[PDB]
Length: 9
Length: 9
Image 1: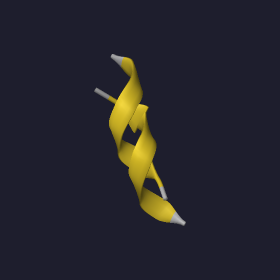
Image 2 (image 1 turned 180 degrees about the horizontal axis):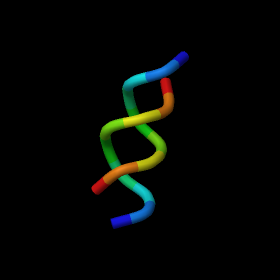
Image 3 (image 1 turned 45 degrees about the horizontal axis):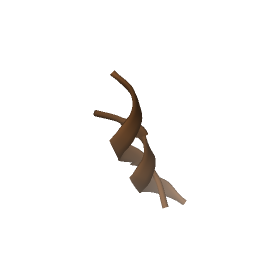
Image 4 (image 1 turned 60 degrees about the horizontal axis):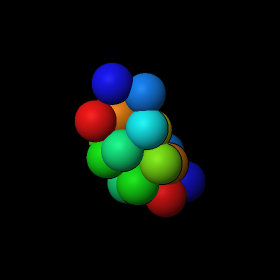
């Protein structure tokens, strides 16, 4: 939980 | 910009 997939671009 | 790759899990 932190980096990875979900938010960003 | 919003959803995608960067933050999450």
